[PDB]
Length: 243
Ligand SMILES: *C(=O)[C@H](CO)[C@@H]1N[C@@H](C(=O)O)C(C)(C)S1
Image (cartoon, rainbow, N blue to C red; front, side, top):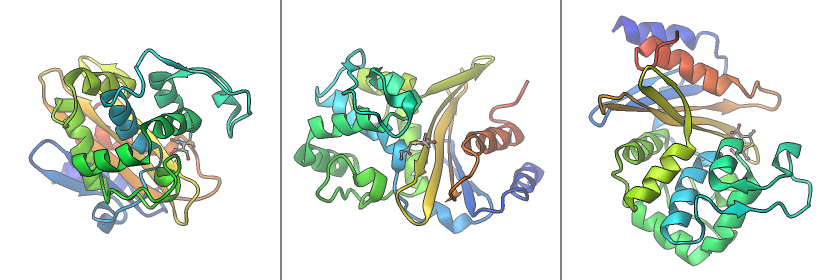
């Protein structure tokens, strides 16, 4: 109860509309400045890389050790003018690498797969390398936590080793034997801009707590806030304490 209060007091800083959803395989809990956001579907943005990677590896469109060579065309961030493996690109949010992946998957296979796994509204439109960045694909924060919780538990409808590979692409840090897995997202090409920070905390016992920060974004917002806010919540909840 007071834990739940200590979490809300963090959201007093946050002028933006936000929601923080947690899941432990039984109960969904909601926190933030605007709770209806948990039931609302938004474009997945870079959080789709999780599903994309899974779909690609499952269908032999790539390997986890394969290197996606840079084409020489300067990308949106100078950081992306480089060669990447799916894991390195996952950490760096290298959009062009996953665009290449989506193109290799193709629109037919991408459609059937998203339908098979029930990922959000399962709509891709006509551009197989754009749907997650500008719609029509949408997904709710509740759908994100249930999806990412299953990845943690190896319960998604994919090969164990495929789920394993994508899981470790999301690894951030550990404290004791509690491990933090996460993925950030910023739907920059839509009004309103959507900000994501989706993941889970794996406690060595075997118990997992999946999480999903979903908030309103604006031009010029601090890129580090989403993660930082999420860690501040995970600390106050007792799921992932600071040192
Ligand atoms: C994916 O959500 C975007 C591409 O539009 C990339 N990821 C962002 C993020 O996770 O913070 C970015 C601002 C690095 S760009």
